[PDB]
Amino acid sequence: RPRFSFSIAAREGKARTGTIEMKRGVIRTPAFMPVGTAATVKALKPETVRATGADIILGNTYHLMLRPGAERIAKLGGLHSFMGWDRPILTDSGGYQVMSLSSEEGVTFKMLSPERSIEIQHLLGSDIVMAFDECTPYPATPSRAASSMERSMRWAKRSRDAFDSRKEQAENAALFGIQQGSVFENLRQQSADALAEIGFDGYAVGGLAVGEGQDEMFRVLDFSVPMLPDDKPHYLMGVGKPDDIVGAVERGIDMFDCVLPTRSGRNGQAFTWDGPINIRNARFSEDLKPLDSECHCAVCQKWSRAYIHHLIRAGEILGAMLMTEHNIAFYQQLMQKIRDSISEGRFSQFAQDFRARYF
Amino acid sequence: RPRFSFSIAAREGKARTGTIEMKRGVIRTPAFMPVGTAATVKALKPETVRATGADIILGNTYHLMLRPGAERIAKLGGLHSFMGWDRPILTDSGGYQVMSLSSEEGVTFKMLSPERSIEIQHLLGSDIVMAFDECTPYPATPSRAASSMERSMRWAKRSRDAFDSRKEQAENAALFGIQQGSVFENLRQQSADALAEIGFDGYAVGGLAVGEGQDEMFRVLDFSVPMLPDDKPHYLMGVGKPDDIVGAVERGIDMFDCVLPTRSGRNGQAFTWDGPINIRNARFSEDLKPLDSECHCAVCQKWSRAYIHHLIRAGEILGAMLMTEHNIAFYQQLMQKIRDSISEGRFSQFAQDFRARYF
Ligand SMILES: Nc1nc2cc3[nH]c(NCc4cccc5ccccc45)nc3cc2c(=O)[nH]1
Ligand SMILES: Nc1nc2cc3[nH]c(NCc4cccc5ccccc45)nc3cc2c(=O)[nH]1
Ligand SMILES: [Zn+2]
Ligand SMILES: [Zn+2]
């Protein structure tokens, strides 16, 4: 199979649908990547993750570089082998996580640099390597975003050279650059230009899903995404409320990752086509209906709201498992519905039908 | 299928192997029943519970009578439907749980009587109904056990009559009486006699796994089990360390339930043929071996100790799932190994081979 080959099969407006062919599998785009932060998609076996329809999962160098550690994962045969997932894994570069969770050379925390970042993701056996960037604090001044963006672009080229330096990783993996510039269009252009000049396999929009709200997020996507190379995937990092995803696809985004389905799943929130439900609610205690009346997932085929209600209220691990599986399943069905409606050129109507029922 | 039919296919010493045929399935004996205390076998889907090889699961009226409640489970189509398990369920009668967890008529707690107990288990749709008894506090004086046992036998006959009173339950379910008498042989005889005079489908030994230690537990089984009707299953409630099970089978016990595989599973303990391991131990951090070198379970086929180590140390739900599944799988393999070695008449050698390696 190819190392990295992105093919757009259909379009509608700025929305695209296609595939990314990678050595470890095909990624159907627009793609939702379940997040597997500690070398697990929480409360799901990889197989279950796969059955929900995910093509690729997201991992973080920051978390794994600490536990169990990058060299150790390498010694253990790589992340894929370690967690039992043999399909593409996208590893975040460590830039956002060192921020929220914890110089020119890089970042010291309790050192992550572009070179080490790439080296770690290589150690992990990452298929898609994220340039190591400086996630832009939001809000931030024009001047601040600018300098923060430009460090990121300098780090982008360093990322590029480190990656290109490692034959094995260059041959088998993909490197995505990350656009920064905050909400500022000219900064966003500057950054897209620098990234394009360097050249990457894919272009992420970083700096969003920073509490800017959907409106301002979409506003930025509106100008930011068309500045990226059309022929490469566009990855909106960390975005995934169902309606965020729809509106970002409408704006040219092909890839998504979000802790929302999993985490909200464990907390009682079930996504349905009629909007999320909180299954803990007493109203579900004798509700024999499945979580969602349409959902094809194993959970909706087998268990009632009443049972899951019971389960979540009792803190039962099976509650978390069922909710999470349903929710990832839901997310994947939405992506599938998005892919098919784009390839059928009715994505517009989907989005409106979706929004209409969901809200 | 029959309502309740116990057939002994082979014997070795006091050990028996056979089947209990019930309307909702066959129970291979000696049987280990995973415990599903809140209408779930913790961190396992029923299907997973089934794949490990369990034929029957244990439920408690005490827990379910409170949450979600017995009438409500009934309204919801029964326990089987509710939790997605369609095979026999054995419901404990509420006698031990009102004790550890919370008159002649019954017990008031913050009222459970023989009649209500049976009515609740009928509401649950229990296949095997436990007489409602007074679990004997241990230790206890001869006089005390005696009076506590005799209330239990009076409750046993009440249990019997209530059960027999409910046509539907009498037709489709089984009623097991429970022998009491503590460590006292004559009390144990008295009780077996009263139970036999009443007549039940099966005979449980209650009052053990009360911290008496394996020695004194086996000592009591030694005289207590032969007093029960040979032609009926013998159920040792709440017993299940792997070596407890082997020694109880050697003493004529056909059925077991124990929270040990599940709970110890969630806490880091993996059973192996070379004895339990605590997977949290640093020694497993780069151990690419499966939990147990022989275990056929999905977990041992797929994941390394190092990964599960990582998982459990990080408090990852998948850690609990994998450990629990392995452990129930282990327990079922032990029961299978016990069944086959009895039917092959080499159960003696198994027990010694087992004990030899395991300790
Ligand atoms: N390298 C890089 N990685 C990023 C990862 C991002 N993740 C997100 N959103 C995740 C998220 C999920 C759920 C709730 C959240 C609340 C506050 C902030 C983030 C939340 N944004 C990311 C941006 C970057 C980035 O710019 N660079
Ligand atoms: N009706 C009835 N039910 C019983 C249930 C019993 N369960 C046990 N053992 C469970 C158990 C599992 C693990 C650790 C434990 C520690 C202390 C006490 C019990 C533990 N014994 C039971 C007896 C009865 C009974 O006599 N009657
Ligand atoms: Zn579902
Ligand atoms: Zn195993």
Image (cartoon, coloured by chain):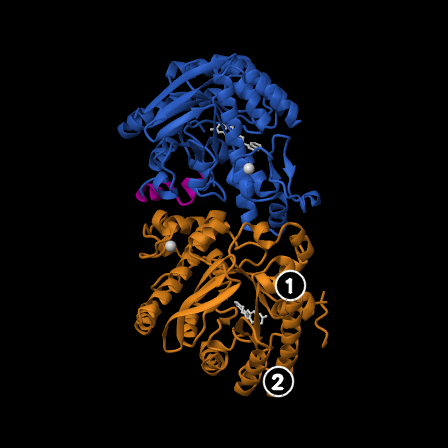
Chain colours: A blue, B orange
Q: In this view, does B323 lie to the left or right of B211?
A: left
Q: Position of residue B308 (x, y in %)?
A: 41, 50
**Image mark for residue A72:** none
The kind of secondary structure element at disc 2 is helix
Q: Which chain carries label 1?
A: B
User: Mark 1: which amino acid?
Assistant: Lys
Please tell me which residue is depicted at 54% across the width and 84% down the height of the picture.
Answer: B189
Q: Which of B218 and A89 is in front in this view?
A: B218
Looking at the image, can residue A217 be seen?
yes
**Residue A63, magenta (yes or no):** yes
Mark 1 crowdedness (10 Å alpha carbons): few <14, some 14-19, many ≥20: few
Between A64 and A343, the residue placed more toward the observer is A343
Residue located 67% across and 58% down the image:
B66
Is residue B316 something that shows in the picture?
no
Q: Which residue is drawn at 45% across and 76% down?
A: B214
Quarter of the image that includes the C terminus of chain B: bottom left
Tag 2 subunit: B
Is B258 contained in the magenta span? no
Find residue A55 and report its horizontal and vertical position in percent.
Answer: 42, 31
| Pointers 1 and 2 in contact (C-beta within 8 Å) | no
In the rendered structure, which disc, 1 or 2, sits on the residue that comes first in sequence? 2
In the image, taking residue A57 as reference, residue A215 lies left or right, namely: right
Note whether A35 is above or below B111 in the view shown. Answer: above
Q: Residue B167 carries which label?
A: 1
Is residue B284 shown above or below A231?
below
Residue B146 numbered tag: 2
Looking at the rendered image, the disc whose residue lies closer to the viewer, 1 or 2, is 1
The residue range painted magenta reads A62-76
- State whether residue B35 is above or below residue B104: above
Provide residue A193's location: percent of width, then percent of height: 44, 13
Q: Which residue lies furthest to the left in this view?
A: A167
Q: Main secondary structure of the magenta part?
A: helix
